[PDB]
Length: 87
Length: 174
Image 1: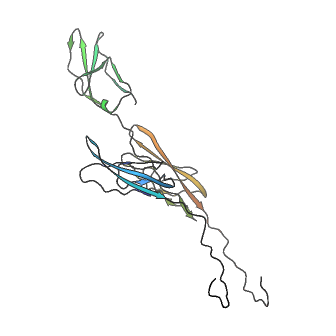
Image 2: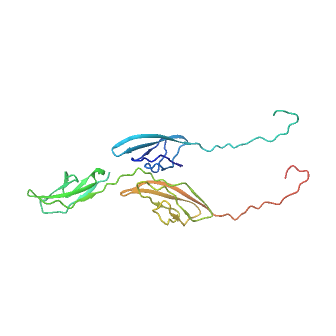
Image 3: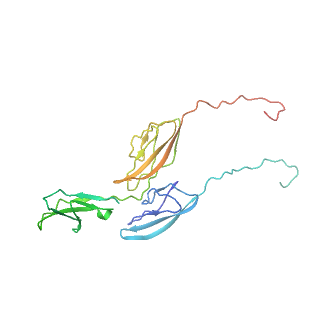
């Protein structure tokens, strides 16, 4: 779960599209929420347009999801050496 | 996708009814005008002309059709709520861009204000219950939904109660 971040336009209306199942709660906002997020990466697109001037300009942003690992740091035990310079 | 249905009052026997669009063009005839599979372009002003024996009367009062669009915003609720010894909380849904939200509940939970994405909830059973966020706009009823849960665990009565310190002599285990 995350949010998007696009720069609002000065004189136009923005719009988001998604890939690989991600869901945008509000595709019309530069700061909308996204709840469906696959693992790995997906590309979100910001398409800017004004009135009849449809699909005027685009940009690409990506969201990367890495699941928590199950391994934890697990170091060995302390040792006690006599006369060694290596271990 | 729904039909627009407008209907004129009955007149004299033999009356012919003609319906006109906002743009002053014909859209069909008869007492009842049905526009099937209506779209947003069919929204707006309509008027009726009454015709008898080659005479026509003044146009009717203008009425309007309203065709609601299905919005692009999906329903979306926030993440799970997990409470320790509490039966009172608040909800968290993301407000829609161009629609109106609504909450429903299960298992007795009470929402103080079902119309708000951030309303309070005071009746909360123990265990879990599912709250639903249903998003709709105008006539486009029950358009999109999402599921959020609230988990309530009552305080336990057991407290950490460790044994007493010990004192061993020559042991490697205890």
